[PDB]
Length: 69
Image (cartoon, rainbow, N blue to C red):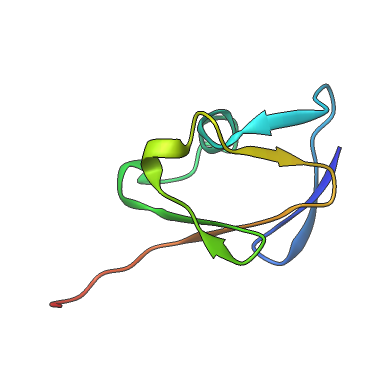
């Protein structure tokens, strides 16, 4: 399947879809504990990572927020 990750082309052979939890682990996203995930321009809630699914053509973004506020 094809998807966009942080604005760039990405491919996942062997899967037609994946939930966010599997995605984070597979891509072994650093400090996944405190990383923010955006799917198709919407910030996701960590509580729904197991249910939220990424399919061919979706755009995912990994962001990290740090600061005193």
